[PDB]
Image (spheres, rainbow, N blue to C red):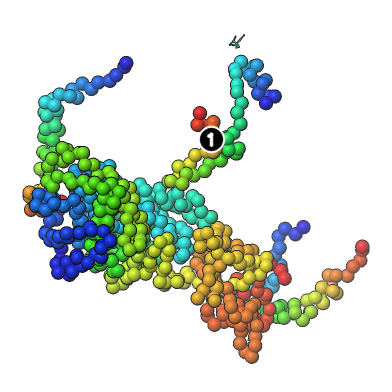
């Protein structure tokens, strides 16, 4: 069972002008079904039972 | 002794409506500057020679630190009861002689140690330290506190019960090391009026006094309501005998009725009132007329309906106490009130308060659990934190999964807080351009934080900024 | 019966010399001290220490 | 009781059995006056004689 839970994340240097809009595009993509669609095509094709 | 009006006191002298029993109190008003023991001994023992009296009531308006002890010695050497009413005669004492039937008007030493803990529960001051000096009675102050702490479901923390043994010369070095070991928000002190100012001088040098640190002292430390030596730090809180509603003429009238209804009531049952020799001598020869029978029921008396019974040590069983607080203007101000194991504090929330922030929460079944306050003690229990609630506020207890995060975070980032449940909406929503709920208060600068079961999304992130998630949803 | 007794504990004239002997050098070192005040004058003159 | 009779024969003493008065096992309770703590039950009779 999982014993260290910490997700991924786009890394940026401190004092970066893009540090806000990058973190607001990810939140919107979760709620639009976009990141539940990339999972369908790249990570979740069953091959063996 | 002191500055007073004779006619004002004498107006209520013959005012006791004691027509039920023929006491006939021949009250005599005596005024004399008798601070020194010589004047007392040459007057008390001469009164019986002139006027046949078997009862003396003493009052004073001086801050003498040993007048009660020297006045008690006359009671031990005689069989005439005497009561201390006002001034230094009402100061506390450790013990009395078995033959010294002298009593006072004032709270005992155990009760004062039981009122300090009765105001810390309301304001949730669960960590404290004790500083005590040598005095006849300082042993009971520590013991009474420990007994109450042991048997209680509330979370009491004790530390630095070190005492100041300031008796040797050049004690500044010794006091500084002892005083530097105090690291508690509130410190309880037990000293004398003169001894207090010595310790307070060292306190300001260290820097302990100020905001974040509070001191509580008993009645005798304050002493006077108008003589402020300007050494007491602002915010000092003390519990003292009521004096605004307990006037000097009223004290005399109340005291006189106690003695009159005691000796006369003995004639009702014993039917033989002793007549001791009215002189300073021949006390041993008059040992036949023992006053043990009189002493049996002189303490247990009643006047118009009340309990004025004294303890065996000579302390009033049901006294009246008030809580006073010093201000910037160096004038004592009334804050609290005590009457028959009841407390009525004027201030619902202590005015004194970046390190102090507000917190808004909300009840959710596995995360934030709200339970009612303990009925037995009227204060929140252990492992839970107090949390207010509107509708006049009501104090609940809050505990759960999210609260443990808040307590653990505040330990490392070292900041304080005070939660309170929201009452307008829940969880946040936007209606016609207005936010209501846990988010509708952060946006209006009434919270500055909000811990609970909030959900991150784009609509809310453009108004407030969230932290790193600690759970998935 | 086994008891105990104190020698020179009941001779009052014995301790008179010892009482003033100890205070003899106590006053000597007290003389060379600053601000040597005096006790209250009489039973009525002063009520302080 | 069957074990007690074995010790009496081995160590050569005599006994007499009496039950506890109140009937408890033993714990430390505080006296109402002050904080004097005394045991009660079967554990408090051993120390009392
Ligand atoms: C992010 O978006 C705001 C408004 O859409 C815009 O003003 C800002 O320039 C954007 N950030 C960057 C780095 O362009
Ligand atoms: C055991 O007890 C008996 C009873 O008095 C006595 O003879 C002696 O103490 C013991 N007998 C032995 C050791 O043979």
Instruction: Tell me the residue at 30%/69% (across/down).
Output: B245
Residue B142 visible in the picture? yes
Q: Quadrant of the N terminus of chain A?
A: bottom right
Which is more toward the observer, B426 or B286? B286
- Neighbour class for label 1 at 10 Å: few (<14), some, many (≥20)? some
**CB of residue at label 1: within 8 Å of ligand 2?**
no
Q: Label 1's element?
A: helix
Which is more toward the observer, B71 or B370? B71
Task: Kindly give the residue lying farthest to the right in the view shown.
Answer: A48
Q: Is residue B59 left or right of residue B161?
A: left
Mark 1, residue position: D44
Q: Is residue B27 left or right of residue B379?
A: left
Instruction: Tell me the residue at 90%/67% (across/down).
Output: A46
Residue A32: x and y in percent read 77, 81
- Look at the picture and state if B98 lies above or below C20: below
Q: How many marks?
A: 1
Q: Is residue A48 left or right of residue B331?
A: right
Residue B233: x and y in percent read 31, 65
Residue B188: x and y in percent read 37, 57
Instruction: Tell me the residue at 62%/72% (across/down).
Output: B362
Ligand 2 picture quarter: top right
Residue B102: x and y in percent read 25, 50
Residue B94 visible in the picture? no
Q: Is residue B280 left or right of residue B416?
A: left
Which is more toward the observer, B189 or B73? B73
Which is more toward the observer, B6 or B370? B6
- Look at the picture and state if C2 lies above or below B182: above
Q: Quadrant of the C terminus of chain A?
A: bottom right
């Amino acid at each position: 069972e999982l014993f260290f839970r910490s997700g991924f994340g786009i890394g940026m240097r401190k004092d970066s002008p893009w540090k806000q809009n990058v973190s607001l595009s990810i939140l919107k993509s979760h709620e639009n079904g976009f990141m539940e669609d990339l999972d369908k095509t790249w990570v979740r094709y069953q091959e063996c039972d | 002794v002191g500055t007073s009006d004779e006619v004002a006191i004498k107006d209520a002298h013959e005012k006791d409506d004691f027509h039920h029993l023929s006491v006939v109190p021949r009250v005599e008003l005596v005024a004399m500057n008798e601070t020194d023991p010589k004047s007392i001994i040459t007057r008390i023992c001469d009164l019986m020679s002139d006027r046949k009296i078997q009862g003396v009531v003493f009052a004073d308006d001086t801050d003498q630190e040993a007048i009660a002890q020297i006045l008690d010695f006359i009671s031990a050497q005689t069989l005439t009861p005497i009561l201390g009413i006002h001034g230094g005669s009402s100061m506390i004492m450790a013990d009395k002689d078995e033959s010294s039937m002298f009593f006072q008007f004032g709270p005992s030493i155990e009760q004062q140690a039981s009122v300090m803990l009765n105001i810390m529960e309301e304001y949730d001051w669960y960590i404290f330290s004790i500083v005590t000096t040598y005095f006849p009675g300082y042993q009971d102050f520590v013991n009474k506190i420990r007994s109450t702490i042991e048997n209680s479901f509330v979370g009491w923390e004790l530390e630095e019960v070190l005492l100041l043994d300031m008796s040797l010369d050049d004690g500044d070095s010794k006091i500084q090391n002892q005083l530097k070991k105090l690291q508690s928000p509130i410190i309880l002190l037990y000293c004398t009026k003169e001894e207090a100012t010595y310790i307070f001088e060292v306190a300001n040098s260290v820097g302990l006094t100020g905001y974040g640190y509070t001191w509580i002292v008993p009645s005798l430390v304050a002493g006077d309501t108008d003589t402020v030596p300007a050494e007491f730090p602002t915010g000092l809180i003390s519990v003292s005998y009521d004096e605004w509603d307990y006037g000097l003429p009223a004290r005399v009238r109340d005291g006189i009725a106690i003695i009159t209804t005691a000796a006369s009531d003995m004639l009702s049952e014993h039917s033989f009132i002793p007549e001791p020799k009215s002189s300073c001598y021949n006390t041993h020869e008059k040992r036949i007329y023992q006053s043990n029978m009189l002493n049996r029921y002189l303490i247990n008396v009643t006047f118009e309906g009340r309990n004025l019974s004294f303890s065996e040590d000579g302390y009033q069983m049901h006294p009246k106490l008030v809580i006073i607080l010093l201000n910037k203007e160096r004038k004592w101000e009334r804050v609290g009130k005590w009457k028959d194991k009841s407390l009525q504090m004027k201030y619902y929330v202590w005015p004194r308060m970046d390190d102090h922030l507000s917190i808004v929460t909300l009840e959710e079944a596995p995360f934030v659990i709200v339970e009612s306050v303990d009925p037995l003690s009227g204060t929140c229990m252990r492992n839970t934190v107090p949390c207010q609630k509107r509708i006049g506020y009501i104090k609940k207890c809050c505990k759960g999964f999210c609260i443990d995060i808040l307590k653990k975070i505040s330990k490392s980032v070292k900041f304080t807080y005070d939660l309170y449940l929201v009452t307008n909406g829940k969880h946040g929503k936007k209606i016609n351009g207005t936010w209501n709920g846990m988010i509708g208060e952060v946006v209006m600068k009434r919270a500055y934080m909000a811990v609970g079961s909030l959900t991150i999304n784009e609509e809310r992130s453009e108004v407030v900024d969230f932290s790193v998630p600690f759970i998935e949803t | 019966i086994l008891g105990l007794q104190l020698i020179n504990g009941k001779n009052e004239s014995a301790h008179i010399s010892d009482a003033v002997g100890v205070v003899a050098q106590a006053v000597h070192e007290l003389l060379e001290k600053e601000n040597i005040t005096d006790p209250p004058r009489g039973c009525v003159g002063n009520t302080n220490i | 009781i069957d074990l007690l009779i074995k010790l009496a024969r081995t160590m050569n003493f005599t006994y007499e059995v009496h039950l506890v008065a109140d009937g408890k096992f033993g714990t430390q309770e505080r006296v109402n006056n002050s904080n004097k703590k005394e045991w009660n039950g079967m554990m408090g009779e051993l120390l009392s004689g």
